[PDB]
């Protein structure tokens, strides 16, 4: 993008990539917290 | 800050962020992140003879 385009425009398009990739990464983290609770619930049962 | 100079009409387009040419490369370059104004008017009556 930045190499062939125009810096003022490259910045807006790179920000779209940052936002889309950040949303993917945040989705990953939310699902790890939801799955971590399931493993902890199982580990509490196994300890009991 | 008030910067003033004289160029050909053809080159007023270079007085703007992210342009190239003799003026913007070698004489008066505005930064990519520019937050001001450009005012330009024709002065044939004053600066040509």
Image (tube, rainbow, N blue to C red):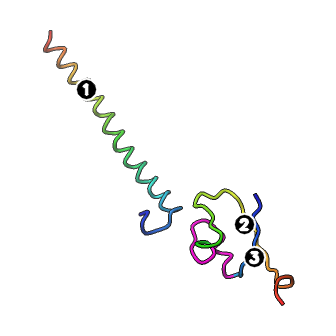
Q: Which residue is mark 3?
A: B6
Foreground: disc 1 or disc 3: 3
Foreground mark, 2 or 3, reads 3
**Pointer 1 local density, CA inside 10 Å: few below 14, some 14–19, many at least 20:** few
Q: Position of residue B33 (x, y in %)?
A: 59, 57
User: Which one is closest to the eye, mark 2 or mark 1?
Assistant: 2
Q: What secondary structure predominates along the stretch shown in magenta?
A: loop
- Chain letter of the residue beneath label 3 in the structure image: B
Q: Is residue A39 left or right of residue B19?
A: left
Q: Residue furthest left?
A: A46
Image: magenta residue range: B10-23
Q: Is residue B37 above or below residue A39?
A: below
User: Residue B38 — which label?
Assistant: 2
Q: Quadrant of residue A22?
A: top left
Label 2: few (<14), some (14–19) or many (≥20) C-alpha neighbours in 10 Å: few
Element marked by disc 2: loop
Give x and y (percent) for residue A45: 16, 14
Category of crowding for the residue at label 3, using alpha-carbon neighbours closer than 10 angstroms: few (below 14), some (14–19), many (at least 20): few
What subunit carries mark 2? B
């Amino acid at each position: 993008i930045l190499s062939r385009l125009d810096p003022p425009e490259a910045e807006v398009q790179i920000d779209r990539l940052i936002t889309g990739r950040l949303q993917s990464l945040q989705t990953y983290v939310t699902q790890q917290l939801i799955r971590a609770a399931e493993i902890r619930a199982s580990a509490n049962l196994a300890a009991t | 800050y008030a910067d003033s100079f004289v160029i050909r009409g053809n080159e007023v387009r270079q007085i703007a962020p992210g342009q190239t040419g003799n003026i913007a490369d070698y004489n008066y370059k505005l930064p990519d992140d520019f937050t001001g104004c450009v005012i330009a008017w024709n002065s044939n009556k004053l600066d040509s003879k």
